[PDB]
Length: 115
Length: 116
Length: 116
Length: 115
Image (cartoon, rainbow over all chains, first blue to last red; front, side):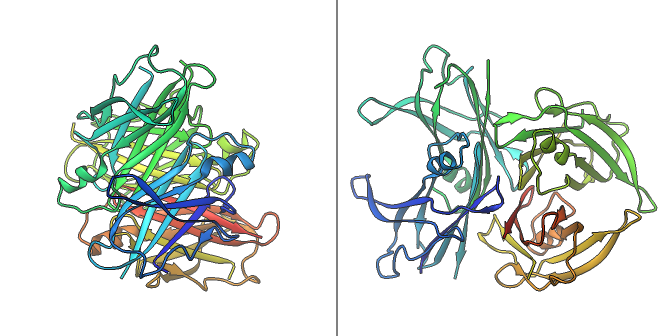
């Protein structure tokens, strides 16, 4: 499992359940080609997006549908979505965890990168 | 002054000087069209991007060039940039401050919105 | 003005008005002795806590009353307060801004330090 | 396991290894009585601090020795430590995870509270 996403709710103090996540890779013509997708579990985590064989060097984008989450809770949000863009595997393969912390008018995202 | 951007360095505890910022608006055909650009000053702030007349209701994108900032200091960071996307002025005119706080493997962003 | 405090609400995207702030210094016998206090203004800022003369080298503590802010809006938050502890002026006089960003189950804090 | 602590490094993109953590409970005379302590693992996590029987209602403090961590890495820090103070179990027992994200001049702390 070379890529995993984990999401938390700063208002309720809970994992974010059933939020949509889309992944893209950048093409030779500089457009974004769809690659993988899913929804977060009851623990706020999304596993099984790609394999070591498929996840080659390149530029990748992760898009989290934050607006649909806050609408479902009846709270008014600021952003359309939350986005992370990064270069992968420049020094060999690694395992990547993308962590996001969510509030209606503010978010943070951190990468935890291992061996 | 209806749109302002402010950037800080969380390693040194200081404002971030000469950082590039580009702004786009969503067109009727779903394309991103160039709206404004500039660089941060000594206080880490960028003023005078637009006017109340020009800044109509729509979806806007603010892209901050965080990779060039880190590379100039000898560091290879995680992110390519920091990007913020939002609907503006849908309940009438407002003033917007977009703030960003930077680390090599993390960033946070916050919006302060006031009624002029 | 060598010490300033600024507070924001991350649910509403707005400055936080009338929030209580207390400051203490560590005494030679290891006790905390009261140094200054005040409340935030309409812009969420608190100015004029001390002077360059009075603000000597030492360990300082800033306590922000976040529980009362949330309770006044009908909310029962996680934290009792937000507290920041730091050594000041150990390489000569500097200006300090202490910023805090508030959610019911989370807070972040940042220091901006400049050479006057 | 009613209480666990997890810590991350925003400069290196890694868990924080071997950082000291102390826990206190507030006494009738308003002083802080020492309760439990330990160090974070290779995954940045600290388990086994207390039990359901011992962890009764009250006000608790968690202190993380952030200054010693940054000194060991040769980077100059702002804060003496990072502190979280909270009331526990007011509506019955819960499981509490205290998560902290660390930079030299800035930190955040979030609570994840379950059933």
